[PDB]
Image (cartoon, rainbow, N blue to C red; front, side):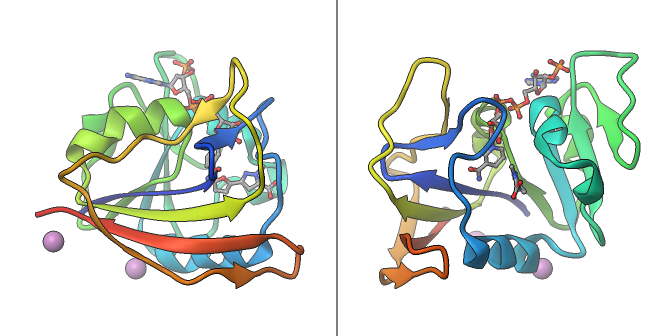
Length: 159
Ligand SMILES: NC(=O)C1=CN([C@@H]2O[C@H](COP(=O)(O)OP(=O)(O)OC[C@H]3O[C@@H](n4cnc5c(N)ncnc54)[C@H](OP(=O)(O)O)[C@@H]3O)[C@@H](O)[C@H]2O)C=CC1
Ligand SMILES: Cn1nc(-c2ccco2)cc1C(=O)O
Ligand SMILES: [Co+2]
Ligand SMILES: [Co+2]
């Protein structure tokens, strides 16, 4: 089982400036619940975006994708292809835009959080992959976060 998990603004923006341009505490708990105990796969830039105290993410098999054959990430496995990182019972690809687009052809689930902020897409932004006709999803209802922002969960799956 290869899943993808991300939070996006409605526009599809997931990253900007090596950061996520919002903070949604509920989503962080949701991400932790979904990924805990499993293999997580991330691009090197997303690994870099994790503060030193959060890397590696506890209780998960942290795997980092990099074209750098020398690259070493303290607390994660560094591999040079996605298939190298996809050795699993359950793997969650956790970002960023590049690695999501690389991983979607091998994914059966996407756990999407949509953040209701009018964040327009800007050149250089990391974007969410757009899910086509093969993706069947169920919409969650709007929720309000402690952060003040409105958000809702999507659970996408394909057979
Ligand atoms: N839910 C969210 O909203 C999330 C948002 N983000 C955001 O995403 C943004 C970064 O995403 P992005 O900019 O796309 O960078 P990525 O995080 O996708 O990592 C990109 C790196 O992955 C490695 N890589 C990519 N393709 C391959 C390949 N085919 N083979 C081997 N290694 C590969 C390279 O590392 P090298 O260059 O070292 O070879 C590349 O630089 C940040 O702003 C981050 O905060 C991240 C995760 C979740
Ligand atoms: C920037 N940033 N990225 C993440 C993240 C966790 C999993 C994927 O991305 C958390 C944070 C944070 O709260 O600082
Ligand atoms: Co689980
Ligand atoms: Co299935």
